[PDB]
Length: 7
Length: 7
Length: 7
Length: 7
Ligand SMILES: *[C@@H]1O[C@H](CO)[C@@H](O)[C@H](O)[C@H]1O[C@H]1C[C@](C)(N)[C@H](O)[C@H](C)O1
Ligand SMILES: *[C@@H]1O[C@H](CO)[C@@H](O)[C@H](O)[C@H]1O[C@H]1C[C@](C)(N)[C@H](O)[C@H](C)O1
Ligand SMILES: *[C@@H]1O[C@H](CO)[C@@H](O)[C@H](O)[C@H]1O[C@H]1C[C@](C)(N)[C@H](O)[C@H](C)O1
Ligand SMILES: *[C@@H]1O[C@H](CO)[C@@H](O)[C@H](O)[C@H]1O[C@H]1C[C@](C)(N)[C@H](O)[C@H](C)O1
Ligand SMILES: [Cl-]
Ligand SMILES: [Cl-]
Ligand SMILES: [Cl-]
Ligand SMILES: [Cl-]
Ligand SMILES: [Cl-]
Ligand SMILES: [Cl-]
Image 1 (cartoon, chains in turn red, blue, green, brown):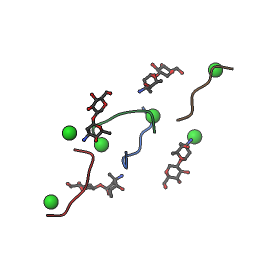
Image 2: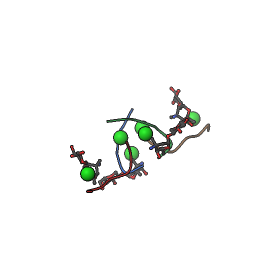
Image 3: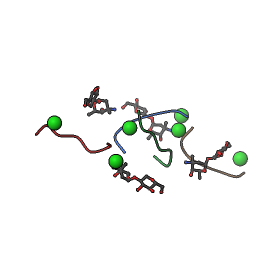
């Protein structure tokens, strides 16, 4: 992971 | 990054 | 930073 | 911590 979102 | 720690 | 993860 | 070194 490590990214974010939210989709 | 974006996480924290400390390890 | 410099550490890693993942949490 | 989080920095390095070495002193
Ligand atoms: C985390 O570090 C290792 C060691 O250098 C790499 O092999 C790996 O690709 C790296 O992970 C990437 C992908 C991730 C977890 N989604 C984050 O983007 C991190 C910062 O980089
Ligand atoms: C990021 O979203 C996940 C779900 O996929 C939550 O479980 C987690 O609480 C959330 O992370 C927080 C803490 C972090 C990783 N240090 C960052 O500040 C993010 C933006 O919010
Ligand atoms: C940083 O030094 C400490 C001692 O104070 C060691 O125990 C540790 O192994 C070392 O950390 C590694 C792993 C890290 C934190 N992801 C970085 O890559 C550093 C440079 O090396
Ligand atoms: C880590 O994040 C918290 C939440 O925002 C701050 O309150 C804290 O000052 C921060 O820690 C600093 C000091 C440290 C651990 N030596 C590193 O430089 C990190 C990135 O920032
Ligand atoms: Cl990943
Ligand atoms: Cl999402
Ligand atoms: Cl750390
Ligand atoms: Cl993480
Ligand atoms: Cl500190
Ligand atoms: Cl040192």
